[PDB]
Image: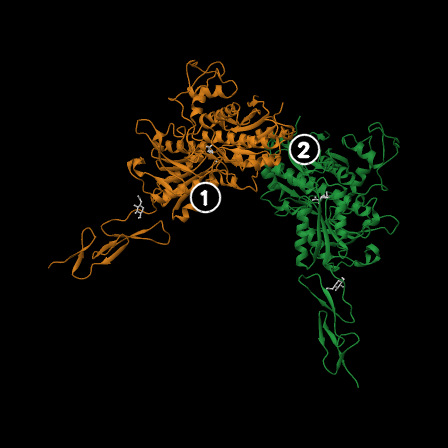
Chain colours: A green, B orange
Amino acid sequence: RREIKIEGDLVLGGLFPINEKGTGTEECGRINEDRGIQRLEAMLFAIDEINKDNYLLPGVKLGVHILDTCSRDTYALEQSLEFVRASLIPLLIAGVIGGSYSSVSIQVANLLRLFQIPQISYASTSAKLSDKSRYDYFARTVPPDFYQAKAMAEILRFFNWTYVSTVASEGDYGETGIEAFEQEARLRNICIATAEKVGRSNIRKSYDSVIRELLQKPNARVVVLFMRSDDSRELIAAANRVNASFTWVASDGWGAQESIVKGSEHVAYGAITLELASHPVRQFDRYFQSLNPYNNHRNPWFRDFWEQKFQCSLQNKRNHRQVCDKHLAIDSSNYEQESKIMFVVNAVYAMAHALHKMQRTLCPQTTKLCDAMKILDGKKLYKEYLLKIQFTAPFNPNKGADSIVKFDTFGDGMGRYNVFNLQQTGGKYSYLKVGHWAETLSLDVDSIHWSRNSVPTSQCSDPCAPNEMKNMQPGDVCCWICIPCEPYEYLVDEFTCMDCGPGQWPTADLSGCYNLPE
Amino acid sequence: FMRREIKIEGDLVLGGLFPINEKGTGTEECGRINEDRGIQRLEAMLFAIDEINKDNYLLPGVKLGVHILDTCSRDTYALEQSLEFVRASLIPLLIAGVIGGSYSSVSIQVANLLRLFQIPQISYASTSAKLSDKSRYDYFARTVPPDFYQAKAMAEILRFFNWTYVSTVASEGDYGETGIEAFEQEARLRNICIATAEKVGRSNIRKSYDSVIRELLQKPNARVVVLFMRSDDSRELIAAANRVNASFTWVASDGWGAQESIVKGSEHVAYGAITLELASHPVRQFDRYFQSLNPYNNHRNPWFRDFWEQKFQCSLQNKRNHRQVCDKHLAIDSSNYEQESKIMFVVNAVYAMAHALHKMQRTLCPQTTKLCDAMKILDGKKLYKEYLLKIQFTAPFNPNKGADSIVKFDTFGDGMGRYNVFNLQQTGGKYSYLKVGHWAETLSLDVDSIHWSRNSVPTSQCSDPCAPNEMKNMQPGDVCCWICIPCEPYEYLVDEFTCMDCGPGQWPTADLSGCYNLPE
Ligand SMILES: *[C@@H]1O[C@H](CO)[C@@H](O)[C@H](O)[C@H]1NC(C)=O
Ligand SMILES: *[C@@H]1O[C@H](CO)[C@@H](O)[C@H](O)[C@H]1NC(C)=O
Ligand SMILES: N[C@H](C(=O)O)C1[C@@H](C(=O)O)[C@@H]1C(=O)O
Ligand SMILES: N[C@H](C(=O)O)C1[C@@H](C(=O)O)[C@@H]1C(=O)O
C-alpha cells in the first residue's frame, strides 16, 4: 500500500506504472525504472519547480497524491477510487496527471468524469481517447495513434514491404492501434500475411506460439508491432529462444527503450521503431541524478528501484547478498532521460497554468485560493484548460521550434514522430534517429543499418525471372505467379507476353523485337 | 454528522437506492422526507427481502442482506453514496447487485459507476430512453419501460382531442429533456405545433418557475401544456401557477403521475389535469405490511421516525425544538395511506435479482442450497447475462397469471411499455385521480368519464376561430395556424375554408350555409 501524499492548497493526483504487471497471483511485479520511476520523479520535479515559481500559481502551493498503476487498468481503477473519495486523511483532487497505458487512462477516465475531475495523460496514445462524448474530462499532451498508424504504414509503403505480419497487444492500445494500421495498409496496397495478438496473463507458450506462426509465413520478413512495452519485451525474448529473425517495425510501446532488447539484442538488431517527437528536459537530468536513497525519502519506491538498478541490498530487501556501495549514483554512464519525460512535465504545467488562470479570474484580489475557488468547478476547469496555450516549461530551449503546449478540440497533442533504428556499431546496442513523420514521411535511408546488412524484402511472391517470365496476379493484389513465355514472345510489359509475330523474334532483353535473318 | 443507512448482513447482499429525502434547498444536501416514493419504496424492498428470506423455493439456503442508501433525489449525492458499493469489493458488505435509482439522472450516473466494477443494477422507476443503450449502460436493467413509448401515448392523446397548439415544459436532466425530445418528435409526425418550449432545472427557485408561468401565459391560445418533469419540479411549477392563479389543462408524464402530494395546496390550479403513470396494480400483501409499521416496531429503518413526524405533524423526543407530542395510537391505514403507484416495480426488481442469483446458485452449486465456493466471488458479467434471460411469474403478490404477469427484460433490459391515463377530479369535495384510459400500443380512453378544467373539453389551437357571418378559414404554410378572410356579401361558405359566389339571381343566406333566390 505505497503512495506519495504531499499536502498543498490544491492537490494533483498522479498515476504511473511504477511497477510492472504482477505475474500470476501477485498484482505488482518488478520496478519499471524508466517509464515508472523516472516519470514519477519528473512530476515531483515539475511540482517542485512550480512551487518555486513566483509567476505561476504564486501563493497557491501544489501538493500531490501519486499512486502506482502496476501497469494494469483494473488496478489503476481501484487505486483511483482514492481520488474521488477525496471529494466527500483524504486529499481533495483538483486534477489527475496520468495513465501511461491507454487501457488504464481509459478506465480511470470513465471514473474521473463521474466526478468532473480533469485528467491529463502524458503517454496514452489510443485514438479512442479523442472521443469527447465518452472521455469528456480527458486531455493529453501526446497525439492519437490515428497518426502513428499512418507513419508506420507509409514506412512499409516506402520500402515496398507489401507482405507483412502483424502482432498486437490485447487492450485498447494494441487493438485500436493495429486496426488503424490495417486500414492504412489496405489503402496503400499492403497485405497482412498473418495477424497475431498476445494479451492478458499470457505466458511463454502464448508468445512462443506467436513466433511459430510468424515463421509459417517466411516471405513476410517484416513484422509490424503495435504492442505494450511489457508485451514487446516478451515477444522479443520469445524470438530469441528459437533464434527467430525478422525486421521489426514497432510503435512507441516499444519505442526507444533499450530495456526491451536487453538480453536479445541480436534478435532485435536492425529493428525500426517509432516514438513521439520530443527533446530531453535538461534541468531534469540534474534533478534525477542528484537523487539517492539518502536524500529521496518522499518516493517510497526509490529503495526498491535503487536495489534493482544496481543489483543492491542494504537492510531493506529480501534475504539476499552483496550489500551496496554507498558511492553508487545515477549518472551520465547508467542513466538516460526517458523519451516521454517532456510530456509528463508539460502535462503537469498545463494543469498548473489552467488553475492559475482560473485563480486570477475568480480571485482577483489575492494570490491565494479565495473562497470563490474553495470548491472547484471541474467542468469549467476542463474548459479553461482546453483553451490553454503557453510556452513549454522553461525547460525547453528556443520558442520557435513550436514549443507551445496546447490542445486539439479533442484534447489531443500534435502528431509528430521520430523513427529510430536499433544499431550496434560501437559494440554496444543503441537507437539512432533515422527519420521522422510530421504529415509526410521523412528519413535518410543511408544511415539505416538493416538486419543481415541488406534492405529487407517482404513481398508475397518471388520476383519473376527476366529472361522470360510475365507477372500474373491471381485473385488478390499482393501475390502472383510467374509464367515463362514462348521463345518467340517478348514482354510488352511486366505482366504481359506478346507474340513478336512472323519474321520477328524477341530481343535478348525481351523489351522488344528484332527482325530475323536468313 | 450522521449519514444514515440500512445494513443487514446476509450470505448475499443487495444494495438499494431510494430518494428517501427530497433535494436539499440551498447549502443543505437533503431536505424533507419523500413519503410515497421514498419511504414506501424503501419498505417495499425490505418487504420483498423478508418474503424472499421466508420462501423455501427461492434462494432457500441463501439469506439476502441489504445495504440501502438515500439518494436525496440528487445524482451527485447518489453517486457519492454508491462509492460505498464498490469499496465493498475490495465493516463493508459485498454487493451482489444494486436495486435502484428512481430519478433517471441518478440511475444513469450510478450505472456509470457500477459498470466499472461489473455490479448489476435494476431500477424500478427510471424511464429515460438513454438507459436502453447497452453500449453505455451494459450492467443496467429495469422493470419499467423507456419513455420512447410514454412520449407516444402523450402525443397520441393530444392528436386525439386535436390539440395542435400546445406549450411544453421539461425538467433539466436525462428524464425531462430526453422525455420531451421524444414527445417533440412524436408531435411533429402528428402535426402538433409547440407554442413555447420551456424548461426548469438544477437549483431553480420561485422566479425560475414564476418566469415559466409568465411565458406560458404569453401564448393564450395554447391552453394545453405538456409536462415531462421530475416529481419535485412538477410540485414547484404547480405552486408557481397557483400564485398568479394561472390555469391550463396539464398533460404530465409519470414524474407527476398520480401523486396527490404534487397538487396539495394548489388543487384548483391542477383540476382537470391529465397525467400518465406506468400500468401497475397494487401489491396487496404490501398494504398489510406497510400498515403494520410504526415507530415502535420499525427500528431497522433509520428514517422512519422523521417520516412519522412529518406524515402526522408529530414530535416525540427525537425531533427539533417543536410542539405537539404525538398520539401513541396513530397508525398508517386505509384512511391516510395509499400504495404508491410503482411499488409493484420495486418488488419485481428485487425479485428479479433474487431469481437471477437463485438460478446461478443452482447452476454453479449443484450439491447444496448454500453459497458454495464456486460462487464465493460472483462473476457480475455472467450474473447480468443470466439475469437478462430471466422469466418468472410476478412475486406471489400478483393475482392471476394470464394478465401477462411475467417479469422479464427486453434485449435492451427494459420492461413493457404499458401506461394508464389519469384525470385529476374532485367530485366528492376531495381531489383524486381517476383512471380514464390506458395505452398499450394504441390509445384507449372513455372520454365521457373525464372531468375537464372549466367543465369544457379544452380547445388548444394556434389561431382564433373565424367569425361565422362571413369568414373563411385559411391555412398559410403550416398546419396549425390560419387566417380568417371575410367573404363578399354575395358569397356563401360551401365549406369552412371556402367562399363561393352564389351566382346570378341568388344570394347567400344569413347563415351562409346556402343560397336563396332573389326577389324583385
Ligand atoms: C519499390 O521500392 C523501392 C525502394 O524504395 C523504390 O526505389 C521503387 O521505386 C519502388 N517501386 C514501386 C513499386 O513503386
Ligand atoms: C378532431 O377532428 C376530427 C376531424 O376534424 C373530428 O372528426 C373529431 O371529432 C375531432 N375530435 C374531437 C373529439 O375533438
Ligand atoms: N503509448 C502507450 C499506450 O498508449 O498504451 C504507452 C507507452 C508509454 O507509456 O510510453 C505505454 C505502452 O507501452 O502502451
Ligand atoms: N420516471 C422518473 C424518471 O425516470 O426520472 C422517476 C419518477 C419516479 O420516481 O417515479 C422519477 C421522476 O420524477 O423523474
In which quadrant is the C terminus of chain B drawn? bottom left
Residue in view at x 75 percent, y 42 percent: A230
| Callouts 2 and 1 on one subunit | no
Q: Report how far apart the C-alphas of labels 2 and 1 lie in the structure.
A: 40 Å
- Would you place residue B279 above or below residue B164 in this image? above
Q: Chain of mark 1?
A: B
Asked if disc 2 is less than 8 Å from ligand 3, the answer is no
Residue nearer the viewer, B117 or B281: B281
| x and y, in percent, of residue A406 in the image | 66, 46
Across and down, in percent, residue B416 comes to: 46, 38
Query: What is the chain letter for disc 2?
Result: A
Residue at the disc numbered 1 = B182
Above or below, B20 against A217 in this view is above
Q: Which mark is residue A79?
A: 2
Q: Quadrant of the N terminus of chain B?
A: top right
CB of mark 2 within 8 Å of CB of mark 1? no
| Residue drawn at x 81%, y 39% as measured from the top left | A286
Depth order, front residue of B258/B518: B258
Residue B491: image x %, image y %? 22, 57
SS assignment at label 2: helix
The local crowd at label 1, few if under 14, some if 14 to 19, many if 20 or more residues have their Cα within 10 Å, is some
